[PDB]
Image (cartoon, rainbow over all chains, first blue to last red; front, side, top):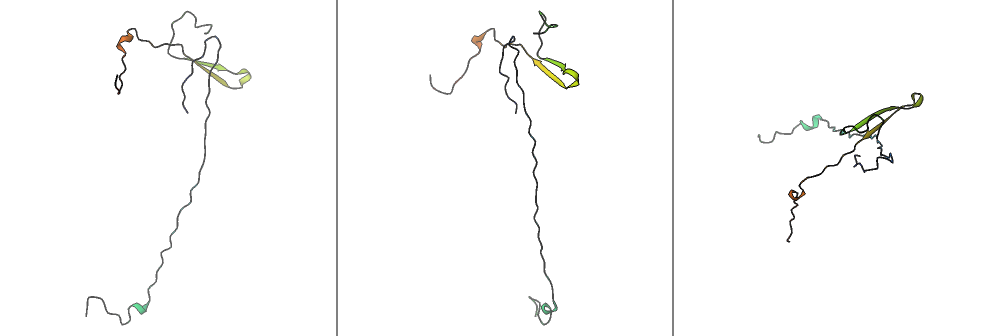
Amino acid sequence: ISLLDAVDRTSRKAETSAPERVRQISFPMMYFKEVESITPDEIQGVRQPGTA
Amino acid sequence: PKMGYANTLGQELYVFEYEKDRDEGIDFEAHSYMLPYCTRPQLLVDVRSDAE
């Protein structure tokens, strides 16, 4: 907040001021659980693609 | 307007330090007494983007 100084009279003796502000926030995060398993059933009797 | 500043050359800003009674704090004052002007106002011309 900056604002413009409004003119006042030397003999009246008057003036201005200014406040201040502070806040706070928080943050959560994301989680991932990629899982996978291998078994002998994927090797027993299955031929490789592209080969005889 | 001050006891020590009367019939004396002015200055862009007047920052004053004052002490509150019985060490209660500090208060400030900032004065200024100025006037910008042009001695040949006929040289100040504004332009507009519309017809006469």
